[PDB]
Image 1: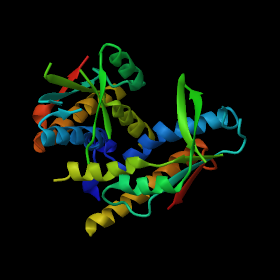
Image 2: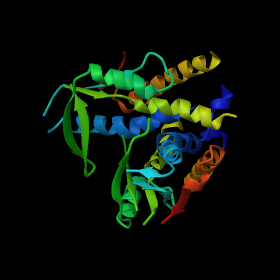
Image 3: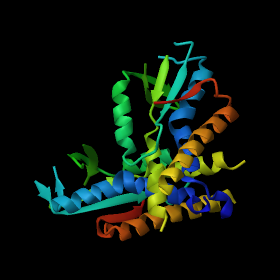
Length: 143
Length: 144
């Protein structure tokens, strides 16, 4: 099945979108905003400048610099919690899985390979968000 | 860059392995067991559904109710696990299996067979890498 062979970045971007991004964007457009009601909403997705070993350390240092309050909204019979600043702050810790997939599935240039994968992860998010009409809701920012 | 083109199942299996399996197994090997008293006999039981459908989470919600678990904690390099007389069964549900359909549906512009083989590929890849790193005895994959 050559057609279902994807980069780990492409695969994890689609997984990250369906898990933590698309449910939040669908709820906001359905209710015209974030409901306990907030009219203006932004989902800020912070991307590290480089993809290095222990991505969790990078995000742990980044989360400390931001102050967030916990909020909750129900969707699909599920209470869902988000960290807000309205600014919904979400850290893609799933980026560590890019290096997890490559190192376990393969038998300088590696740092270049990770820089290309981080690009494809971000561009995949912009594409599916553009497809679903969520481009004004989702803002990707760097450190 | 053709070499880093994998099946979504293989990508997610290695992600699930590094996120949960490998740290829990490495902790067992270092402590000679599960330190909460150390339980010397520890096995991780991974429960997978028989079919990859939509709403795999509802499948796991159905599977959790049939199993009785107690929360335990340990520290590796704080982590929480659900366990089940000297022999401890660490129970884990790979809810990441929902990502296989998330990947194929989003990354592509009959379908039951593809998800069927992807579930097998997830299980095969997980066993393959666990066998490589020497954690095969601590891992057991079963279904409902």
